[PDB]
Image (cartoon, rainbow over all chains, first blue to last red):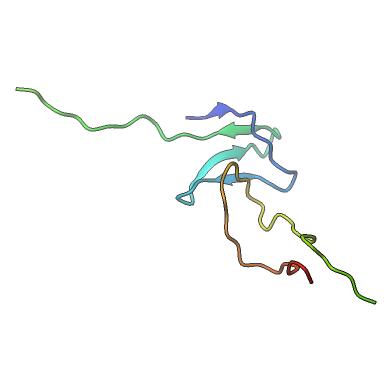
Length: 49
Length: 34
């Protein structure tokens, strides 16, 4: 899920990576703006019976 | 002559951003106090 980011990228910086080597912030090639990256919601499913 | 480079010649190694983290990189650097 994208989201506008207040993050600062240097002019040569296009991808901001995570601890697990995953991009958690990107810069759109067309418009030079920084977008926040977040994997969609997930979780276990427990059935109570 | 000679002089001491205390903590000079440190740059950003890669084209990636990081925040509030300590990162370790192997790259051509200027040794401290050289």
